Picture 1 (spheres, rainbow, N blue to C red):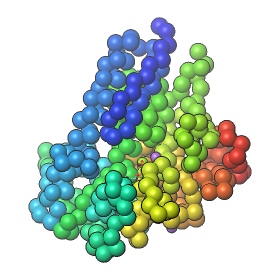
Picture 2 (picture 1 turned 120 degrees about the vertical axis):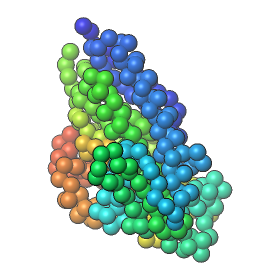
Picture 3 (picture 1 turned 180 degrees about the vertical axis):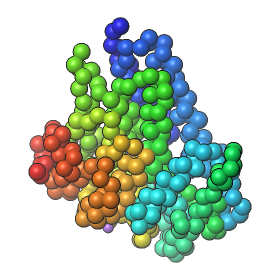
Length: 330
Ligand SMILES: Nc1ncnc2c1ncn2[C@@H]1O[C@H](COP(=O)(O)OP(=O)(O)O)[C@@H](O)[C@H]1O
Ligand SMILES: [Mg+2]
Ligand SMILES: [Mg+2]
Ligand code: NA
Ligand code: NA
């Protein structure tokens, strides 16, 4: 039995999603797994999407201030994990920020900053503690979500790609695959080891925060690990000489003013890496290090505006700088 390498990529969930697999299984089995990966992404776009009228999440948001809504176990679990990171991060990551994000989402389209009072009003409808998750303990009991605060809106943009990368890994493993690189718009999961007959760690690239995005500035060698990056120049618009990026500080209702250009989180679960990358970007370097002490199983890599790079002890020896303008502090 020979090793073969496969990849497939499609535009779905608003970005380019690519999965690369090495396998000795019959090619038909790999093709079937990849078919299911991309069917899953299509289906989940219709569950999780914040910017569509026909998604399950949009239906949930339409019931804010009303009765609990039945959701499937998967969406319930994702919301539970999102609220966990909201609590642990002091709301730096906030999955109920839709009232504010939606104003900024039209801002992007219109290239215009939201009004002050409108923005001040939106911040009053973002209390994630008023998302009530309930699930009965008896056999087959439904899972429900209630948005108790009038006009509050869920937006899972900062955790959905991580969730989907984890769901894809679970699917690949269900198909008896153990070597893959999952890349959902840059949200990476490195499953197992790649092939060279030699088995090698995956060399995951981290971009220059200001890069055209072509070349990575650094690579990190990893196995069975998600690598998720949140950064200041990945999505933004400009107006009158000021840049407004897409990661909001919930305290100000404005794009976060932070001391790092990007934060990359390395974790066994991409859900966790995605939520933490957002929280850490909002919190800034020192407070991020404090938060991360609560998660011993994760590592982090910070790129500063002066091109210094700091990486935690669990990954620093695995980092290689490719763009010599950057310096890895040791
Ligand atoms: N502080 C925040 N907490 C949670 N979600 C946020 C926050 N700010 C913005 N969002 C939503 O999450 C998205 C940012 O997600 P993030 O994972 O940080 O970046 P990326 O889009 O590169 O994956 C935004 O587009 C918005 O939908
Ligand atoms: Mg995130
Ligand atoms: Mg993300
Ligand atoms: Na990103
Ligand atoms: Na800040």
